Each structure stands twice: as C-alpha cells, then as structure tokens.
Image: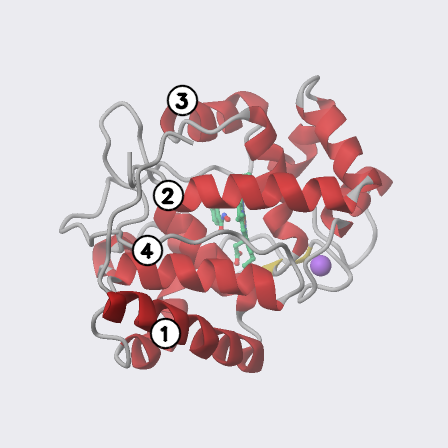
Amino acid sequence: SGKSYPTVSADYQKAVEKAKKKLRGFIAEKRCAPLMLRLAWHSAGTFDKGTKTGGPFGTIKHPAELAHSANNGLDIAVRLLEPLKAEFPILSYADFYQLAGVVAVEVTGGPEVPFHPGREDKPEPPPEGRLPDATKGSDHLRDVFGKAMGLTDQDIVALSGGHTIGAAHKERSGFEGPWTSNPLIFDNSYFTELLSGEKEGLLQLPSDKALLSDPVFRPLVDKYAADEDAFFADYAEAHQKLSELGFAD
Ligand code: HEM
Ligand SMILES: O=C(NO)c1ccccc1O
Ligand code: NA
C-alpha cells in the first residue's frame, strides 16, 4: 500500500532466496527465533515519519545503537548472524536482518510475511529512545507506533503478539520469563494468556496489560484470542508494514 518496490538484479534475488533457506535452518537449530524477531523489530521500530529518520536500514549492527538500553542483548543476535551474512556479501544488512525477522516468524509456525528486497544500508543510527517503554500504557504506545512509526491501532495490537514467542531476561530489560507456555511456537496464545490473567511462570508487562483496558485495543485482543486466523492475517500485514517503514515510498 503506497509502495513502489525497487528493482534488484537476478543475482540479488538469487541471494535472497538462498539466504532465506540458510536462515531457516540456522534459526531453527540455534533456537534463536525470538531473539531474531526482536532484532528485526528493534531495527525497524526506530522510524520517525515526520523526519524520515531511522527504520529498517541495517543500523542496528552499529555498536552505538546496540548500546541503547532497549537493545540490551541484541549484540548476541548480530554476532550470531555475522558468519551467515558473510556468505551473502551482495545483500544489504537491512535486507538480511528483515529477512531474518520474517524467517523467525515462519519457522516457529507463524504466518508467511511477504518480503521485498532492496533496502539500502544507512550510515548513521537514529537517536536513542524511540522504542517503547514496557512500564507505560496506551498513550505511549500510540505515540511510538502511531505518531512516530505511522502504524495503526490494529497494527499495535497485532505486533504486540510478537511476544507470543520468547521471553524477557532480568539481565537485559529486568523483566523475566516467557509470555507463553510454548515460547518457540508462534500462535495466538499471547492473547489467551493476557486475558486469563497472571499465571505463575508467565510474564505480563504493563505495556501488554494496557491493551486490555483500551476501548480500541481490547476488541482486537478479544478477536485474536478467539480467532487465530484473524491474528495471523493482521500480524502478517503489520509485520510487513513495520519491515518496510521508510522503504519503497
Ligand atoms: C508493544 C510495545 C513493546 C514493548 C513495551 C516491548 C517490550 C519488551 C521487553 C521489555 C522485552 C524483554 C527483553 C529482554 O529482557 O530480553 C521484550 C522482548 C521481546 N519482544 Fe517486545 N516489546 C514491545 C513490542 C514488540 C514488538 C512489536 C515485537 C515484534 C513484533 C516484539 C518482539 C519481542 C520478542 C520476540 C521478545 C523476546 C526476545 C527473546 O526471547 O530474547 N516486541 N519486549
Ligand atoms: O525488547 C523490547 N521490545 O521488544 C524492549 C526491551 C527493553 C525495553 C523496552 C523494549 O521495548
Ligand atoms: Na508461544
């Protein structure tokens, strides 16, 4: 929607296809899908529509951006991918990381998020502080996803469902544990667990709980808890948009 994707060479397209396969096997074996989804989303989620700065242009590999507190632990993800990236010198880091995020969702059983190549790596990381704060609520979520990224309220709730895989770590954010009973399985359980309340061994952030009390977010939580197909459709739409912020406009 509103996108005009660039032309890339046949050899570039060949590399995308081969890298997709290599990433599947690597991410599945290493059990790092959630960390790779977090990497891709943290790279993309810095987009500010007003200034057209940040976004999915490969800058998350820069030591300066990895040092942002919201990126605690993503240095591990960058290191894990570097040997594989080196097998695909023709690819931009931006394309590679966004492809890794799409693959992370696929190999855990989630929707097939469309992918288009051609992002060009940008020289300078954006300023720290654009990623969302786990202790804040719905006004903050709309500031970050809406006023900065330019995504919709539907996209906020669907993308929050990325917590359906993975966990927090007390040494990284300070929060601790998985949102779901099957942290390597991508399904609608994040919403089921959010709605059933606190269960021992499972995590809810204040930012997750904010979805339950908001008049626009709550009907979406309910929809996704009742209808995984609907969640998968809206998730794929939102993740594609996120992965393409500032790209091919
Ligand atoms: C809605 C606002 C969000 C907030 C406040 C938030 C906050 C957090 C926090 C505090 C952690 C734990 C980090 C750690 O301690 O390891 C985390 C992890 C994670 N986030 Fe988010 N997040 C948000 C949105 C998203 C989005 C949009 C996605 C992707 C679609 C996402 C994907 C993930 C994943 C997969 C993990 C698990 C990482 C792992 O298992 O190592 N999050 N998030
Ligand atoms: O990993 C995160 N989000 O996915 C995250 C981690 C720490 C602080 C804020 C955040 O948004
Ligand atoms: Na899960």
Image location (x, y in percent) of residue 147: 40, 22
Residue 74 placement, left or right of 66? right
Q: Residues within 10 Å of mark 4 (few under 14, many from 20)?
A: many
Q: Look at the numbered discs 3 and 4 and tell me whether their residues touch, using CB distance below 8 Å.
A: no
Q: Amino acid at mark 2?
A: Glu
Q: Residues within 10 Å of mark 1 (few under 14, many from 20)?
A: some
> Where residue 117 is drawn, which disc sits there?
4
Which residue is tagged 2? 244
Could you tell me which secondary element the residue under label 3 belongs to?
helix
Q: Look at the numbered discs 4 and 2 and tell me whether their residues touch, using CB distance below 8 Å.
A: no
Where the C terminus falls, by quadrant? Answer: top left
User: Disc 1 vs disc 4: which is toward the camera?
Assistant: 4
Task: Say which label, 1 or 2, has the lower sequence index.
Answer: 1
Q: CA distance from mark 4 to mark 2?
A: 10 Å
> Where residue 81 is drawn, which disc sits there?
1
Q: Classify residue 149 by image quadrant.
A: top left
Which residue is tagged 3? 147
The answer to whether any part of residue 161 appears in the image is yes
Residue at the image point whose x is 70% and y is 42% from the top? 231
Task: Say which label, 3 or 1, has the lower sequence index.
Answer: 1
Q: Amino acid at mark 1?
A: Leu
Residue at the image point whose x is 34% and y is 79% from the top? 84
Q: CA distance from mark 3 to mark 4?
A: 26 Å
In the displayed structure, 169 sits above or below 14; it is above
- Which one is nearer the viewer's eye here, 207 or 105? 105
> Where residue 56 is drawn, which disc sits there?
none
Q: Amino acid at mark 3?
A: Lys
Residue 44 placement, left or right of 177? left
Residue 22 placement, left or right of 107? left
Task: Say which label, 3 or 4, has the lower sequence index.
Answer: 4
Q: CA distance from mark 1 to mark 2?
A: 21 Å
Image location (x, y in percent) of residue 83: 31, 81
